[PDB]
Image (cartoon, rainbow, N blue to C red):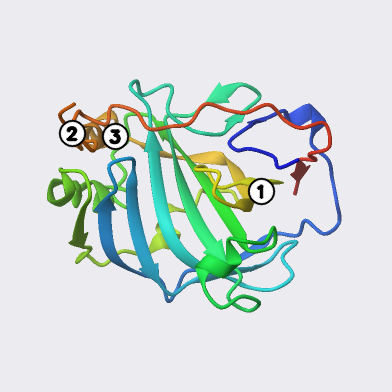
Amino acid sequence: PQQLSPINIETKKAISNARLKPLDIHYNESKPTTIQNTGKLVRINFKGGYISGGFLPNEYVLSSLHIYWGKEDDYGSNHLIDVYKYSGEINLVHWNKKKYSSYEEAKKHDDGLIIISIFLQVLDHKNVYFQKIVNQLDSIRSANTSAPFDSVFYLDNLLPSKLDYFTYLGTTINHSADAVWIIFPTPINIHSDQLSKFRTLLSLSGKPHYITENYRNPYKLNDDTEVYYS
């Protein structure tokens, strides 16, 4: 069967494979175009950027960034590692443009999508790179809104300090497609004030309510889903 995402990664059960070389991340050419409050989450759309190397058959192009958080700073990510939840989670969605015609075609195949997870950890540290995103939220307060992302922003500045990863075959968080996940256990550090600003965003209409949390609870791991560690 499909493996529904997200999941708890049990580190003692993760397995090794020579294929798991470090990823080659190439966000030089990445530029955010617009930012949106979809009524569920914050999405930033990108033009440019790709990942390659690692266990990948070829390059996958970057398309979008999603952000998830919780009601409290200590409980906000989608994925867990050994039943530890981080403060929040960024997902970077990439698709197999080499093989498929559009993201919509790519979504239909288990080699179509690769999603990178970067955890957020609230640690009383104002993160100047993450602040670029925070400082756009005032423009997308209502649900189903869009704004130009004008500020210069280098996506590679949100990469964790260490890029070892877990990988498994799961699904997108809305379960509309299979997706291979690349999960970095090392989080990036942010400040409580920064995460707080996401909770000002409004849901779709009773009347709209604050999106105080938008993570999805984890699903059980299928007996035949293997989790690899690089």
Residue plotted at (71% across, 42% down): 2
- Seen from the viewer's position, the closer of residues 112 and 11 is 112
Q: Residues within 10 Å of mark 1 (few under 14, many from 20)?
A: some
Q: Which residue is mark 1?
A: 164
Looking at the rendered image, the disc whose residue lies closer to the viewer, 1 or 3, is 3
- Seen from the viewer's position, the closer of residues 65 and 188 is 65
In the rendered structure, which disc, 3 or 2, sits on the residue that comes first in sequence?
Answer: 3
Give left or right: position of 19 versus 195. Answer: right
Q: Which residue is mark 2?
A: 200
When the figure is inspected, residue 215 is found, relative to residue 183, above or below; the finding is above
Which quadrant holds residue 151? Answer: bottom left
Give left or right: position of 114 versus 28. Answer: right
Q: Which structural element holds mark 3?
A: helix
Q: Position of residue 131 (x, y in %)?
A: 26, 48
Q: Which image quarter is the N terminus in?
A: top right
Give the CA distance from mark 2 to mark 1: 34 Å
Q: Position of residue 46 (x, y in %)?
A: 38, 67
Q: Amino acid at mark 3?
A: Leu
Q: Position of residue 61 (x, y in %)?
A: 53, 71
Residue plotted at (15% across, 29% down): 207
In the rendered structure, which disc, 2 or 1, sits on the residue that comes first in sequence?
Answer: 1
Which quadrant holds residue 156? Answer: bottom left
Q: Which structural element holds mark 1?
A: loop
Can residue 132 be seen here? The reply is yes
Residue plotted at (48% across, 49% down): 91
Q: Amino acid at mark 1?
A: Asp
When the figure is inspected, residue 119 is found, relative to residue 74, above or below; the finding is below
Q: Which residue is mark 3?
A: 195
In the rendered structure, which disc, 1 or 3, sits on the residue that comes first in sequence?
Answer: 1
Give the CA distance from mark 1 to mark 3: 25 Å
